[PDB]
Amino acid sequence: GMQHPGSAGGVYETTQHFIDIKEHLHIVKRDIDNLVQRNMPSNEKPKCPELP
Amino acid sequence: GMQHPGSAGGVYETTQHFIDIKEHLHIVKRDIDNLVQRNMPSNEKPKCPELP
């Protein structure tokens, strides 16, 4: 009964889901890093023009 | 063909895979915190220099 053929895939589909989530979390990680790098609080405080 | 299916290590595979998502999620979660704590309002204010 467990040896007869049937619908297959409960570990193989499972592992493919693990890779897809890891890829999606990597894309989210990269997009957060790009947004953070575009919001740099460097040593460039707002240069108000000096009065003549 | 039951006690020796050649897929016992899959039991060691999938659960390990779970930890991967957790780690990745944790990384992503940390990044989200590194965004959120950088977008929270603060008592520090962009004080423009006072006019003489």
Image (spheres, coloured by chain):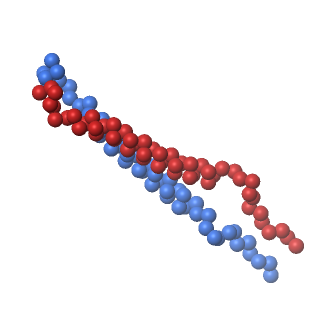
Chain colours: A blue, B red
Figure quadrant of residue A2: top left
Residue B6, image quadrant: top left
In the picture provided, is B31 more to the left or to the right than B7? right
Is residue A13 at all visible to an observer of this figure? no
Q: Position of residue A14 (x, y in %)?
A: 30, 35
Give B6 or A13, whichever is nearer the viewer: B6
| Residue at the far right in the pictured view | B52
> Residue B22, image x and y in percent?
42, 42
The answer to whether A25 appears left or right of B3 in the picture is right
Residue appearing at x 77%, y 66% in the figure? B48
B30 shown above or below A5: below
- Residue extending furthest bottom? A52
The quadrant of the image that shows the N terminus of chain A is: top left
Task: Examine the rendered structure and indicate whether residue A48 appears above or below residue B21.
Answer: below
Q: Is residue B42 visible?
A: yes
Between residue B12 and residue A3, name the one nearer to us. Answer: B12
Q: Quadrant of residue A39?
A: bottom right
Depth check: A37 or B31 in front?
Answer: B31
Look at 45% across and 54% down and name the residue there.
A30
Q: Position of residue B9 (x, y in %)?
A: 23, 38
Residue ranking furthest to the top: A1
Q: Which residue is drawn at the image coordinates 74% and 57% (left, top)?
A: B44
Report the label total: 0
- Residue drawn where x is 14% and y is 31% of the image: B4
Which is nearer the eye, A5 or B16?
Answer: B16
- Residue A40 % position (x, y): 58, 63
Above or below, A40 against A23 in this view is: below
- In the rendered image, the quadrant that contains the C terminus of chain A is bottom right
